[PDB]
Length: 99
Length: 198
Length: 49
Image (cartoon, rainbow over all chains, first blue to last red; front, side, top):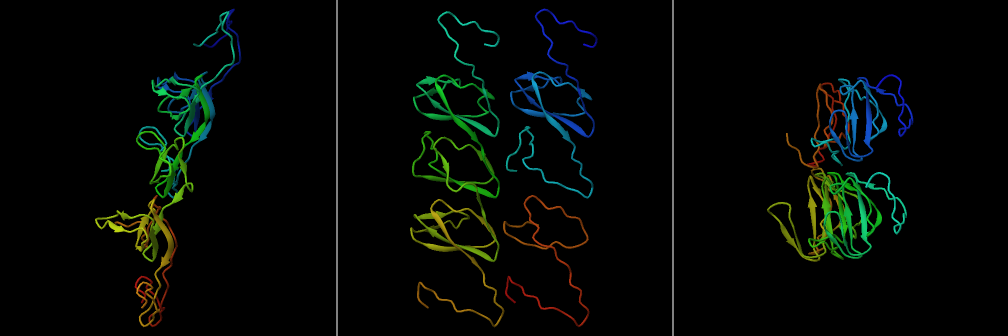
């Protein structure tokens, strides 16, 4: 909630946390602190990692159950460019190791 | 239980113990302090060892009846890699001592307790048509690559040639690599058949 | 065309190639220009000639 906030007697203020702004050329690498649910409603187990894109939100504030591992600059290939991906992610969402 | 905890008069606090986080590239090597039951419900005798994977739990806290021997990084083989495992674990869950197993292809597994790799990760032999290998049988065997699964005896030699990919068996030794010798018409070399003398 | 785990083969022409994941580029070649009544000696190392 936006405005001015009075903490309760039992609550204490720790710090302000501002959103990370997402664009077409950027994504956000997050790790689960514990098991929880995120704003997409998708369930997150301890330790597993994912990316949040600008198709998810334009501004994301890291939850208390999330860890910001870093910002992922996009990889663009031109019509004269290719690449090879090591350990690609498969259909089930796992890295396919050694592939 | 999460929250804040008051110990009883007879209880005392010793220390906080946080979970170990498990992933696809990691396992946890535990030893039994005593006989007990773990969270899978599987029974554990004193001293025996096992691994906990991310298919068991994503967070495991070591029990009071367990010992953390260490964290096991996964062993991944690519489609050009093989390995040989020393003292593999058999069907009954025991290390098969003095035995070995050749594990080939792109695969990922954890070295269980007691198992071991002989020479690390290794490279499969890809042979051109101008390249061959002289193979030696250590035990009597029968190499299976086609319908011509030929039997050999415990001291044989034989050459394998062609465009193909070979991994040594557990009872075969590579002794040499050979190259075809290029020769034009009206050109040659003298060969001896040391078996027959000629 | 099917190939086996140790083959070689030359790809030529005006075209655009990306290597597969199970193919290795080992060399680049150029056609050798030759006028009529001019030449070079080639060996077929497979057959020897």
